[PDB]
Amino acid sequence: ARCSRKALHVNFKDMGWDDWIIAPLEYEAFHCEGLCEFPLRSHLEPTNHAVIQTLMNSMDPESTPPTCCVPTRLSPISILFIDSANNVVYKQYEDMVVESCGCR
Amino acid sequence: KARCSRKALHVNFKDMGWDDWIIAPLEYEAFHCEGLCEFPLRSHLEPTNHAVIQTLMNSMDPESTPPTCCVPTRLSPISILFIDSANNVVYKQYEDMVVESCGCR
Amino acid sequence: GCNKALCASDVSKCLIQELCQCRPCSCCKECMLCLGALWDECCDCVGMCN
Amino acid sequence: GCNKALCASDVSKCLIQELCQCRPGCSCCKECMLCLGALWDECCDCVGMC
Ligand SMILES: [Ca+2]
Ligand SMILES: [Ca+2]
Ligand SMILES: [Ca+2]
């Protein structure tokens, strides 16, 4: 129920990227979703600002909104594609897969 | 409903019950991040490649993929004078206390 | 304007390639190359219309 | 076991002080109790230290 990492399958043809991405045709990127209420676990590695906001949100939710569950660590994947200049490129793209989620 | 942006957030320590161990300051501006994170994501803020892709999927079928979220991407510190658990008086700089910029993630 | 249904896929293509991320200008021309025919209909999505 | 209304203020006090952030798999198990004081009994479950 609380902030956690969930599955997210990325299919490039579904996004209309099959015309420039050669391989892979799909990959798991995951996504972060869940509640961010007191207590924020340290598995959320929260900022001191996030800790305070969560407290204020718990005291008066009408006045202060809660923090949000977002990715805190991301890993890369390699992609073979055709750039705008029709060159074939095998590049490692950063921040493509979610490894851990946290409230911020 | 405006897009992701930095908004005001006044922190009053006595209101939070921290006046019994924080000497000064008793209040400060911390700001907060809130707003819509839909395509297009402000490209000058350099959002992560994952946020870019998720935003695209959310634009393709928002019913199936949820959007990214507006959170702080750069925080600055403030100094605080308090009494620690050992009754020692300490003047320390606390990190990640004030929001300087917001972004969709 | 920025046609989200027409520009979502191709504009995102240029972002993950680390293009169209400067502000007016240096990358204004490599960005135009990436959008191609959609430059007219999608330049506003990245504010590169000049 | 965690009274959120009773423990929100003091538990958060010890977190921003970088206490109660270790795992019992223990170092900070004792410094955390010192920070909570009388509320250790009523708030230990909020950090899984009991
Ligand atoms: Ca296409
Ligand atoms: Ca108190
Ligand atoms: Ca055209």
Image: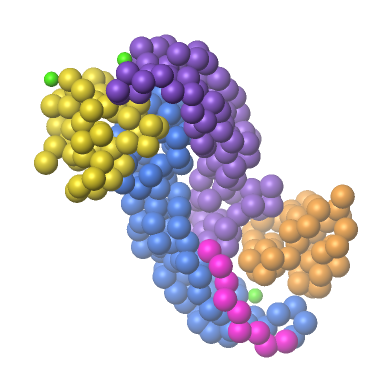
Chain colours: A purple, B blue, C yellow, D orange
Residue A67 x, y percent position in the rendering: 51, 50
The one nearer the camera, C25 or B91, is C25
Residue B87 x, y percent position in the rendering: 74, 85
| B92 in the magenta segment | yes
Query: Which corner quadrant of the image does residue D21 belong to?
Result: bottom right
Classify residue C45 as left or right of residue A58: left
Query: Which corner quadrant of the image does residue B91 belong to?
Result: bottom right
Q: What residue is shown at x 67% (from left), y 88% (from top)? A: B89
The one nearer the camera, B1 or C10, is C10
Q: Give the residue furthest to the front.
A: A87
Ligand 3 shown in quarter: top left
* Callout count: 0
| Position of the N terminus of chain B by quadrant | top left
Residue D36 x, y percent position in the rendering: 76, 69
Q: What residue is shown at x 56% (from left), y 80% (from top)? A: B80
Q: Give the residue furthest to the bottom.
A: B89
Magenta region, residue range: B88-96
Whether residue D9 is visible here, answered yes or no, is yes
Whether residue A34 is visible here, answered yes or no, is no
Looking at the image, residue B4 lies above or below residue A56: above
Looking at the image, residue B88 lies above or below residue C19: below
| A47 in the magenta segment | no
The one nearer the camera, D10 or C27, is C27
Looking at the image, residue D8 lies above or below residue B20: above
Q: What residue is shown at x 57% (from left), y 62% (from top)? A: A48
